Amino acid sequence: KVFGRCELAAAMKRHGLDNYRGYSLGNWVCAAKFESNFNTQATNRNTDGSTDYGILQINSRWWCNDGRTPGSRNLCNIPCSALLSSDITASVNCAKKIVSDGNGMNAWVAWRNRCKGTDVQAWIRGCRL
Image (cartoon, rainbow, N blue to C red; front, side, top):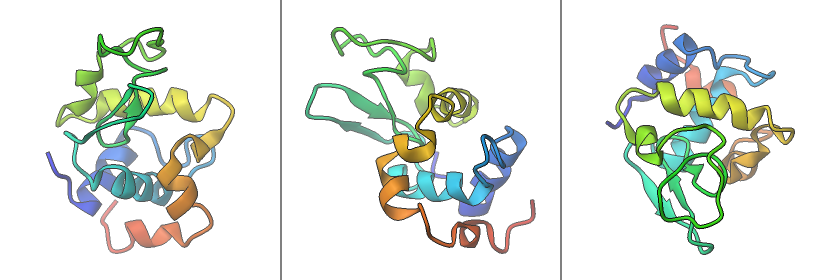
């Protein structure tokens, strides 16, 4: 599923991401835009052999099991395919663990390079929340 900007903002807000660990909703919408272009089915392979899955591009080296990343962990206790669903619940629940790991949203490279320090409120402007 390819979300609209305000549709995703509302789903993220309903799942408790607004101000989760101090990160306002606009940060999460901005991260999703640049990680996946709002597409729940996005996948990208990394040079180490791990793969990133879903709207927030969660990586199989640490967070989910895809059966093809040797020596990896599955800290969210989910198959990576669960992160590609049109229902974002699994992605949001796993993202909450990632952002609590100690590095905040810096774990998302696109957030660090394209959202951090910008006017992220713009990503929710005009939405009925």
